[PDB]
Amino acid sequence: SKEYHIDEEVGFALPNPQENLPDFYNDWMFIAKHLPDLIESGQLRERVEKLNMLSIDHLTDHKSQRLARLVLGCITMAYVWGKGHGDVRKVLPRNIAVPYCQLSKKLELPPILVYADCVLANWKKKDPNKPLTYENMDVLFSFRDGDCSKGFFLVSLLVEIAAASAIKVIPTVFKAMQMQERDTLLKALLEIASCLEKALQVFHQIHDHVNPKAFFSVLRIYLSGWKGNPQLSDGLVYEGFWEDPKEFAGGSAGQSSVGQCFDVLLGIQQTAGGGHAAQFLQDMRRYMPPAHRNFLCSLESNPSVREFVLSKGDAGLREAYDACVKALVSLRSYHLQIVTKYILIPASQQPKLEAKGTGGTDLMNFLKTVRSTTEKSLLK
Ligand code: HEM
Ligand SMILES: N[C@@H](Cc1c[nH]c2ccccc12)C(=O)O
Ligand SMILES: N[C@@H](Cc1c[nH]c2ccccc12)C(=O)O
Ligand SMILES: [C-]#N
């Protein structure tokens, strides 16, 4: 939390991000706040084209810059894909592309919508006095009518917030290890285990608030990017800023720092091996914010928790360590059931070889590999 930008309450998410931008950027905000109206009519592309270029000099604080990144991101997805039928643009106008790339270079992120934009910085609460919950929360931006983006982004965000309770315990783990405190370390790991068990129960909410057929058909194509995607094979041309088409992967909770945090914390070597699964999870750290990228680096630059627990010859300590790994295996085993209900079954129903995700991976091969690596890390 010191320099890593991690909150006790909300976790990796942005605590109370801005809703309104400054008065200078009202032209972007009007396109963002009315994305379903402009895109359904079929008048979005002409409005983005007919819009004079603007500088990014008047964005003082950090919260404004990520709001503008979310705004510019949502328009860029909505411009490229459009109706979600097939008609797409290989080139983005220089009036929006240049300020977005300059803003992207400043925040050290790529010029595309990412998990940090559409989940972590895309929320408010209705009544500030009430706590964090779906009934007292709402998104800032949506793509279409009946896309279930409110239910989607908040249920993703609420599971991120569930893991916040575990992230604050990590300083206790490494303090207990270097000072040789068995009881502190055992209780700290069980707390992390219980917190990750609670995050799975928050996942269950997704069935209530997100419809499968709505999600797959309309929302999923807006979250999709242009890295190894048949529609934009060479990539997306950022006119003015760049020379050629540049490939950039779509949004995914692969870009969440929570997923990769507890694998690194528990010594689950996902990023090792150099396979197609390991190659993806390392690449997605460049799609995370710079502060959370440093946090994962910080956890890797610490003594191994796995090696410590194995050395001690302690049943209770291994058991507490396994509780964390079993919690990750449960979350991943449930996440596959979501993928079956929200991708596989919807994909078979639509009319006219392995399926590609929004991030670009062979999802069924990728997720089962990543879950398998987690399960092998169990002790006895
Ligand atoms: C309708 C809901 C969801 C669907 C359809 C879905 C689908 C997928 C797919 C296809 C991937 C593979 C990467 C890619 O996009 O190419 C993936 C990865 C991932 N998803 Fe989800 N997902 C959903 C919700 C969630 C939620 C709510 C979380 C966490 C709060 C989550 C965490 C992850 C993580 C961490 C990865 C990276 C691989 C891993 O660590 O297991 N997903 N997801
Ligand atoms: N990222 C999830 C926890 C998690 C870790 N690995 C996962 C794999 C799939 C789904 C979720 C997870 C959270 O915020 O609590
Ligand atoms: N990767 C998912 C989409 C997805 C799930 N959670 C996300 C969070 C942010 C951006 C995209 C997503 C898919 O292929 O269907
Ligand atoms: C989940 N992407």
Image (cartoon, helix red, strand yellow):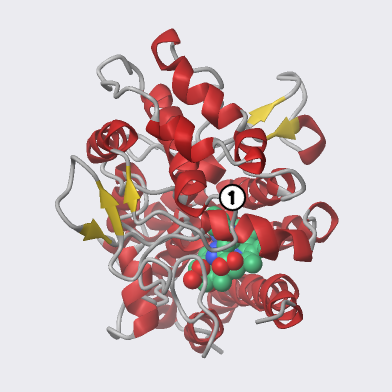
Rendered view: 131 above or below 212? above
Q: Residue furthest right?
A: 208
Picture quadrant of residue 266: bottom left
Q: Residue furthest left?
A: 243
Residue at x-position 71% and y-position 78% = 340
Quarter holding the C terminus is bottom right
Picture quadrant of residue 335: bottom right
Residue 11 at what x, y percent from top left? 53, 42
Whether disc 1's CB lies below 8 Å from ligand 2 is answered: yes
Residue at x-position 28% and y-position 37% = 107
Rendered view: 35 above or below 54? below
Residue 294 shown left or right of residue 142 in the figure: left
Q: Amino acid at mark 1?
A: Glu
Residue 353 shown left or right of residue 247 in the figure: right
Find numbered disc 1 in the image and state the secondary structure of the residue it sits on: helix
| Mark 1 nearby-residue class (10 Å; few <14, some 14–19, many ≥20) | many
Quarter holding the N terminus is top left
Rendered view: 286 above or below 186? above
Q: Is residue 41 visible?
A: yes
Residue identified by numbered label 1: 160
Residue 36 at what x, y percent from top left? 66, 38
Rendered view: 10 above or below 222? above
| Closer to the camera in the image, 100 or 150 | 100
